[PDB]
Image (cartoon, rainbow, N blue to C red):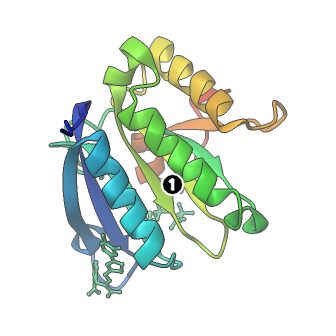
Amino acid sequence: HYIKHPLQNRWALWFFKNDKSKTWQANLRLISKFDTVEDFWALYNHIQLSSNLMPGCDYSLFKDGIEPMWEDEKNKRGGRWLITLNKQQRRSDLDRFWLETLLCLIGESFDDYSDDVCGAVVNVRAKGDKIAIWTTECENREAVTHIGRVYKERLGLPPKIVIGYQSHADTATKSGSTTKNRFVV
Ligand SMILES: C[n+]1cn([C@@H]2O[C@H](COP(=O)(O)OP(=O)(O)OP(=O)(O)O)[C@@H](O)[C@H]2O)c2nc(N)[nH]c(=O)c21
Ligand SMILES: O=C(O)/C(Cc1ccccc1[N+](=O)[O-])=N/Nc1nc(-c2ccc(Cl)c(Cl)c2)cs1
């Protein structure tokens, strides 16, 4: 006898293929959804086993009903904690960071503040990979800084590695690199 183990939330995995030729929204595809521990690992292990990372090919895991874009009702007033990797952290750090990020989400690692979490995004870029946790209200200093503190600790980043929280509204009018931060941790 084998019972499945429900997650607190249902999650959706999205794929994105970079192409500045086409409008941004056109490059997004919903892969599948899951709401159990078993189904999470089945999907995670399948991607690790049968797929290869590719520059310009992003994955996003968001709560059911939240599209992984600024436009979404649940993201428009929100923002993200951004982790920027060096080019050499691609190997033997990116995979660890991403899985640890996924587990923060589905395990609701931020306690009552996990409610403010929308999802997470990994960008694979030759310029340097990026991982981010998106939250729903960029002005909720309490929730945002708590999520940031726990997230940084969970990833084991050295204290002198300062990570920043960007409002999506600011990002939309500049760039994730030149976008100034609302908070640091
Ligand atoms: C997350 N996101 C990104 N874009 C567009 O895609 C561009 C690249 O966004 P990016 O997140 O892929 O970062 P990248 O490393 O490619 O480059 P940089 O951040 O500019 O340094 C952005 O400049 C936006 O124009 C977006 N456009 C819309 N409409 N909605 C979104 O959520 C969104
Ligand atoms: O043109 C492409 O390169 C495409 C198609 C695409 C996709 C989105 C936007 C545009 C386009 N396009 O241009 O046609 N690649 N699609 C991919 N899917 C996976 C992929 C999905 C799901 C799981 Cl479970 C796994 Cl293991 C791999 C890896 S790559």
The quadrant of the picture showing ligand 1 is: bottom left
Q: Outermost residue, left direction?
A: 65
Give the left or right position of residue 96, taking residue 111 as reference: right
Closer to us: 158 or 175? 158
Looking at the image, which is closer to me, 166 or 34? 34
Q: Position of residue 19 (x, y in %)?
A: 38, 81
**Quadrant holding the N terminus:** top left
Residue marked by disc 1 = 174
**Kind of residue at badge 1:** Lys
Residue 138, relative to residue 162: is it above or below? above
Q: Quadrant of residue 162?
A: top right
The residue drawn where x is 79% and y is 38% is 161
184 lies left or right of 169: right
Q: Is any part of residue 70 visible from this angle? A: no
- Residue 12 in sight: yes
Image location (x, y in percent) of residue 33: 19, 52
Residue 156 figure quarter: top right
**Mark 1 Cβ and ligand 1 under 8 Å apart:** no
- Residue 5 vs residue 151, the one in the foreground: 5
Which residue is at a point 49% across and 22% down the rendered structure image? 144
Left of 70 or right of it: where is 160?
right
